[PDB]
Length: 562
Image (cartoon, rainbow, N blue to C red; front, side, top):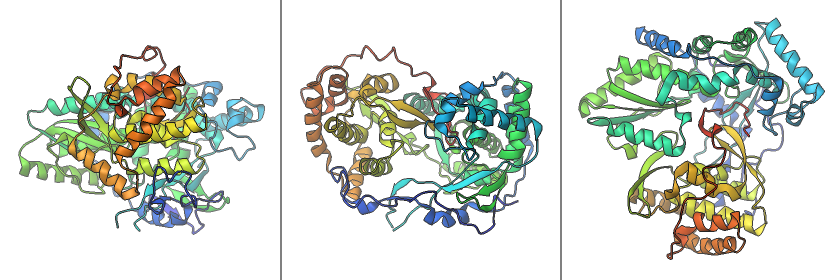
């Protein structure tokens, strides 16, 4: 069975596609080598199509069934609620793709008669029809990267999603399930429950619990394409262990057969492009589904491989396992056996995995633990990453208007990092000052969910999320310092010392404004003065609403929070 079948109809764009930085960047002030920055377009879709299209052979064993049953017994403790139309409507991002049935995201959020009417009709239809495949749209996604160190460019990812009406119904039937079940099933292994500070803590603690730790990330090639119809049905079998309202159970059953296992792909012109028999990227269960499936196959493969004292951390298709070593040679062998197992379960690797005996050298979720020191000199651990993509996208978002602001997300998730503090914070606060946009809330994504956040709130958010040490870190590791340096060289970003300069001015302009703006000056930019102003815990940090921030992943799920 093929992940995809294609009729020949093109994957088409819906509007003009921008592929390059504007002719004279609105901030060469961030980045000089504009030619290094690019966005993906539908022009590269057929390249992705070729990579993403293959036959899935799948052989399940006793290990897999054992783990599945263990997973199901945990799911059996769960009681899930049906969401009302209203609650599901309020989870719809203001800029979610409009319905073909003559209403859009705003109409849904407003509970307009036409939208609510269609939605209800889509719900009844899930009860009245348990078989007919539900239409989807396939599109080339727009994402910005830095060119490979070789005119090497990634082709566009392909997104597949059903109509806005179906999407609201998914929320009603499955939002509570996808938010609750994964922690219930996978426990400490479910990544999305963790803030950056909590994730690093769990990693570092797992590391130390091993007499002699060995760790490895595992990169599945095109995970979404490796998800089989069987995988999707096993996923449902897990879901079905929840206590569920009768209509939720039927909605789940119908959605599974009519939407999740596959169905026809329609381009933006309304032409039939082909047929999907693998995971769709743009449905509510994509993150939860991918996580359960990765966890299930990986845990079974750990048993097949006789890996010992495995502790896994799973985020959708991102997998990192830490275990007890048996010697360099036996580790290598066991890992090869882990890979042959995952392969039989239909998940071959992209890059073959490698045992790693230094926690700091393992990268998972595009990130790695590193070490620095706080004011008191004490050792502090934090999560970082190669800043290349974050910087490219910051430059793109500076030059072209963008609906979602990755830079704000990266500042929140990576607030303690050397590059987020010196470049990103300095750069964007400067722009915001000049345009008096400091008070205006912006949209950003955290674990796939959309949030609307006021920049004048970063100090609180950062403190409660990362700790007061997020404002004092110094003596960053050599490797980190080199990685950043190399990156500024690549993209033509001015050197750190220059940012220290721009920072002093920004910080001074902030302090002169008093109030929240002043707090941003003291806390966010205290790294820029040698006369380091003593930083005490912020009053607001404690009395804010940061609950729903790290509960579950909603990547591709059309989810809008608060």
